[PDB]
Each structure stands twice: as C-alpha cells, then as structure tokens.
Length: 223
Length: 223
Image (cartoon, rainbow over all chains, first blue to last red; front, side, top):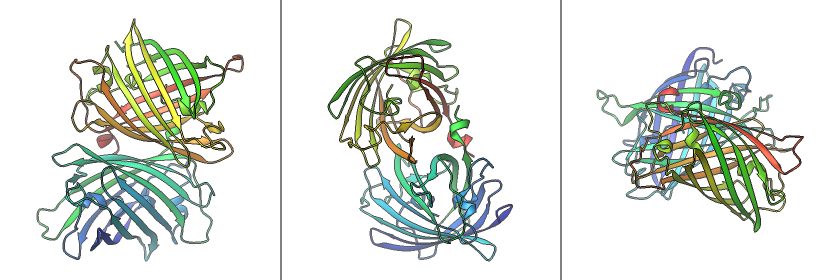
C-alpha cells in the first residue's frame, strides 16, 4: 500500500491548558522513500501554542524500512495502529496524545486527540518561542515487553527563538487496531528530519512540514 | 593531542546502594578515527551490579568530530572538563556520576565518582541481567543556556538477558576544568557503538569494551 506517494490527511482536536482548537492537514507520504509533505491549517482560528509542539503528534508508517528490520507500522495496515505519547517539556507542561493511524479510501489518516496541561504562562510553548526550521531527531523503536506492540523514547531539542534549546522528552507506544498478524521488531532507531515553513501568501494560521524518515539498524550502522 | 592512538586510563570509585567497589581500565582512544578499546578490571573483587550500567560512565573527547561542528571536548584539553550525569532507569534506581576528563603525561584519564541509590533487589541492575554485546546509542550534544559549557540527553536501550529492553535516561553536563578559551557547539548528535566481551582466559571480574564515536550534523545528515 506504501510503494509510492499516497494522500496523507491529519485531523487534530487539541485542548491545551483548556484552550480548544482544531487542525486539518493535507499532503502526501511515500513509505518507499520515507518522505512526506503536508500543510497544517488551524480551522478554529489560531493555535494557542507553538506549532512546533504539534508537529510529531501530526505517521511513522511512512518511514523507509530496510528489509532486515520488522516494519510494525506497515504490518498493521490497512486497519492500522494506536500511537500514544506522553511528552514532557523541561521546566514546562506535559502533552497526553492519542492517535489513530489508519489506511482508508486509498489514504493514510492520522486522527489525533492532543491534550496538554501544566504549561507555564511565560514558557516557550504558550509563548510560541520554538522553531523547527531544519532539525534532525533520533527516535528509539522496539518491541514492548509482551511482544504485542511497540514502545519508544526520544528527545526533541527544539530551537528556542532568542534562547538556546528546549528538550521535550517523549515516551511512545504503538498497538495494532485490528486482530491481524503484526510484525514486532527488536531495538532500532529512526533518523528523522523536519523542515517547517510558512506560506507568506497564505492568510490562515498554518505551517508547512517536510519530514524525512529512515529506520536504522544502529547496532550495525553506528560501528 | 588526539591525532592518533593515545593511552586511555580509567579510575572509577563506585558506591551503589552502599556497595563500594573500584574499577581500573587501560586501553587506547583515537580522536581522529573516533575508536577506543579498553579492558576494565574490578580491583576490589566483583562489581556488585551490571557491568553494562558502568560503561558510559567509564571519554567523548575521542569522538570523531567533523570540521563544521565545534568540538567542545578537544577544545578543553589538556586541562580538560567535568562530565556529570543523572542516569534514571525505568522501574529502577538512579546513578549520580561525576567525571574528571584530563590529558596528563601523554594520556587521557577518565576519573569517575559513580554513586547509585534506590536500586531494586530483583531489578536488572543489581540482578546483572543487562547486555551490551553490540548496541548503537544516539547522544544529543548542545551548548548550555549560558554558553560556558555543554548539556546533553540520551537513552540507552539495554538488552535484558531473558527479558526485552530496559531504558536508562541520561541527563549530562560538561564544564571546562580550566580558564582557557573553549569552543561551544549548537545542537548535534553522536552516533556511538558499544561492543562488550569477556576474556575467558582472564580470571578477575572484568569487561572489554570497544566504542565507535562520531559527531553528526543530524540537522543536515537526517534530510
């Protein structure tokens, strides 16, 4: 299903320190090259927080997997998987995020419930002081202890506009939505790249995201 | 000072859940290739915990740095730097670690105070149920907020013998020991590899470690 560009559609309902907002993204992902491009629009007016804080919540199924690592994400399709994260910001609040990642009508949908609490008034998140202009991130992927799904961990070192860097710590799980046979990997990493940009022509609150995604047998490739 | 193999000497005084032990390592590191080899011996009898839990505490100065990233570690030599870590194990205790990394008499010394508390009796650390046979780790390196030193973060996904994987979360700082001019980088990563082995000939409690260390401009290389 993932040999070639396919539509990538995102629906995020957000609730951060009791500020409710909706985001819709349309673009494309290519699971054989590990590339995607998508434009996110806030449909309820303006995001009450850093766009950058939304980006990883808004499709690791598009990751370019080598043939020697089990690709859990593609193995669950078309029914797909649940992707859940706790994201903890150094000196700031916490996001609780639940995603349904499914293949429907020839398209990959990321449907996201994005909740945040404890965020600080003069913090980088509510202050919108974060930047992902061009940034590499390494994500740890492995089988959960029961061998029914995935767990993972990673940091993002967000650029802080007029500051230094802000670490957000992510804990993730992925569990299949269906009862079909799934493929469980051992420990590996994703080398991921984000570039975020704004259309100066566009008048609505939005952000354009390009990602690169590659699964890496770091146990071999780091030697 | 780091163009070619030079002696690498480690002295670790350890205190884990009130169990005191000493480790001495001798080997070599090569800062131009980013390789090192060292054999660690417990001099007080036996390590009262997983060797694997000691390995990253027991010389990022040996990291192969490209010319487009500031190499803080080599910029501090010969006086060298302090390297401090809090290491937190999922469902287990915490290590507090202070290192002095100095160049003395043509050799690179890592002098380590390794403290651990809250470790669980039937846990993977005191139970010695961890393995680093062949494992890749990605370390985040960046300038601290004051621009006087480094901060960093990383996970190690330890193999658990007869289990799955155990995440240890590391927070690190590096601060110069001297008053000399130091070179402060922006965010990048190290792709590091560990291979641990035992000499079946050797009769003392020991472990042999080979590391690969490369500094990576992930903001470019992950695209």
